[PDB]
Length: 315
Length: 323
Ligand SMILES: Nc1nc2c(ncn2[C@@H]2O[C@H](COP(=O)(O)OP(=O)(O)NP(=O)(O)O)[C@@H](O)[C@H]2O)c(=O)[nH]1
Ligand SMILES: Nc1nc2c(ncn2[C@@H]2O[C@H](COP(=O)(O)OP(=O)(O)NP(=O)(O)O)[C@@H](O)[C@H]2O)c(=O)[nH]1
Image 1 (cartoon, each protein chain N blue to C red):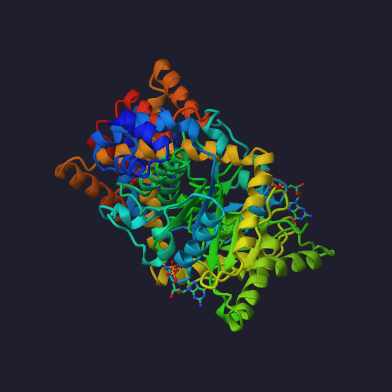
Image 2 (cartoon, each protein chain N blue to C red):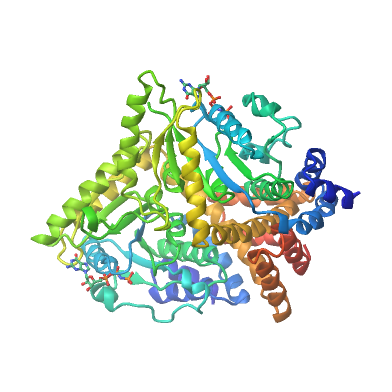
């Protein structure tokens, strides 16, 4: 019953939230429709959260840093969602149980809620389904939404376009990442000597970033040092994110960014549906893959590809 | 007469080139269809050119630098096309004459060929049209294709994705007067050229700016890349730095041709323009009548206004199409 699902979701019921999400992430069109009204209906309870995107190479203490940061926040009374975006999920069907235990503490904290990357046809669709899932979390009372890049593909721009603040975690020992960053945090600044060489590296990143013009005069990206493993610097790291929130709330820039992202996700969903017509049948898929291949092979022009494809999919 | 038009264009007939371009860039579907087979037919004669994207804030000296650079190139026997991408041409009908006071020499040099930005429903569509225009030029025998950003809008990615090499022009001045690299431009840039480095005080301030940019880039550029983006100083107005600027561009082409990276990048740009065009058709369908544009805009307004969800907007949109 969707009325009950809604009410219990609004009441903060973890099982109702998990179930609404399942339907919103579904690759069945009938399921997705079913919960469109529900998300729309609870939209006025969304948005009262800090959305942070977090990235860094595999091997930088990302999951560790998240487990620790998230635990600090649940201890102080926050309810924290951790959602993944993984471009490989455009080729897998998604994951039933995901990989919760990379974050040992959060994985068992009922003040947390951890979800793996949804499946969809395009990266745009994966990210858009993630926005819808963020809205459900918020409506169920999660006030911190962490969205992390997982895998090796290009998810950084999408994660940044899903959140208010984009956090880059770096080691002390992809170009585009720097200009997405609202803050860099040099990790593994261990009390024993790691602090010296991460403080060095932070001066290098801090020096270089002076040459980039930030998108707003309201905020100048800082570079900091932390230890994710021993919990160092995590409190001040969070206080900078809070400070960003207060400043860009006062100027209306948090809201203006979100409005722009939302329209972007709307168009991404329109384009996902179009893409779904490419796999409408084997014949349509064959012919459209060969149009694309022709263009990618240099054999016919982009415009000829485009018209072949447009005819095939009824456009 | 398309058959002669083709043969004339392949022979380097400039009037034929102008004519095919006006069809390719047309906002009339019947027109665009007409020349589709022609471009497809001349494809094996395209690609033998160096394609350079050029950007910079208004006032930095872009038209001046292109005028001086293109002229050097034409004196050496190159045929030089200068095309534009203007994001505001999604809101205009495009320009008929374009702006050429700025390129006084090239505007009369019959070894050059200058075109204003085409008009389309979406920025992707404008840029896609510029790609087809680049192909027609190449087929007519142009071996240097310069593509510039126009105005202050967000067209840099589009130009970067239309060319082999992306050149950023910057103002001189360091310390508190350092211009700063606009959000997005750092990752696109294959070289920075600090312009207005005029004999005397210009060159001092430009050299200062340069070392600043140069050190930052060293820090931020991963070492894997076959190419390390240089920073250089030039004066577009007084001709300084231009042979050196271009020698670096040729070095890029030689290196990345060896590793197959020029051809690999083009093939992914091409697929991207193919999809842009697919999405421009979709968009056209959403402006096909007053009632539908109204409904579309209302849907988008609902999402931007925080009144309805993105997926609910997209569902309303999708109905209006029959999708
Ligand atoms: N010395 C030190 N080691 C750390 C720190 N944070 C993480 N590590 C270590 O780095 C290794 C990789 O950690 P992990 O957090 O899984 O990195 P990740 O690959 O980015 N996480 P994910 O599972 O999402 O990919 C682990 O063995 C972990 O103990 C730190 O602050 N200091
Ligand atoms: N002193 C000096 N002035 C220059 C140089 N290059 C261009 N200028 C001057 O700066 C002004 C702007 O030059 P212009 O080429 O029109 O700049 P633009 O970047 O093409 N502007 P827009 O993007 O709006 O078309 C002109 O007065 C021009 O003479 C230079 O190397 N030195």
